[PDB]
Image 1: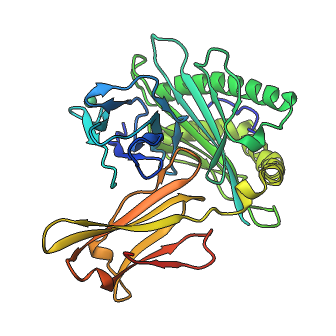
Image 2: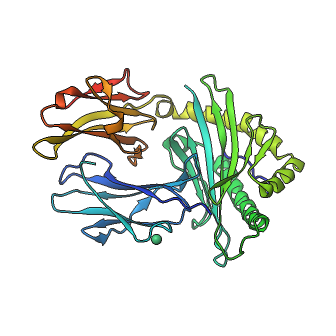
Image 3: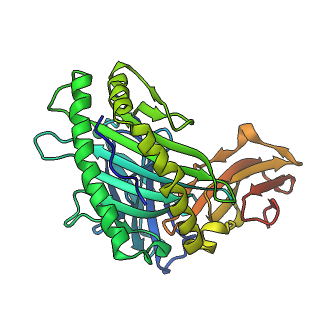
Length: 9
Length: 100
Length: 275
Ligand code: NA
């Protein structure tokens, strides 16, 4: 399953 | 910005036998950026309903796609793949050879 | 056996034509098992391998929401990175993401991965310690300071050591022979006269999984490295792979040549000849 969203760069 | 020229191979899923259902593949790989145009040609004419794999990439970030269609090879029918990409000054056409 | 899980994201801006396109694919080893495309009619995570179809609706729902949120996050990242590099707001740019876990036979984490490329160039990467970043340039150092303050590495580490490992173990249990048992190549040698004095021998490997393979031509049991034409390994379209190796030989000397095939699916390395 995918990772929960990152902070933006 | 990085620009990498696509590698192209055109080939059948199974060894060709005239009159037997098969898949015609055009594998484009090693390219950047991802914008690319790939057509499968039968006797010079664009084949419709050609499907492709989901956009993926290699460890060096270069993209790859498989374009494919179901087809029945014959003696006379000529197949090819036509690729357009920002790195190519003209479209690249690679002919299907059943021995490669 | 040892195994890996990987997710691959591609975001491509198109200023003036709407929000960037976001595509994700997931792999276990060399098998693609999911996709998401932000330009689909009703974007959702979709199965691409039979063994993932058994996951319940809560799985597909959670993942779909993640991809939709990540697409918006990548759109913000692309805005920030054209700012960092002082680039035109009219042009199309690419943000790629690649993450996942390598496990050994016991299913324990060997190595975690979380890394990014901007316009095809490495930008920032989580180090092997899963605690620190390597930035390619002063732009990527802006991202690094942001992610250090936000404790991003701890979020990545928790996933890589936890969900990544646990879900890869699950997919291996449910994929069984499709993922754990290598499929050996079907092999044959073909012969193509060029002239009265030269012929091509071509060694074929078809229908093999995983993609890793070695094909070598030998003359009297010595590798013909400098004289072998080797095509890049290519997908058949049915989850298996193909490769061939060819040598041009003098007519009547074909008996001196053998093709050597090494693949995980073979009981032992194969020696083939024209027959
Ligand atoms: Na072009």
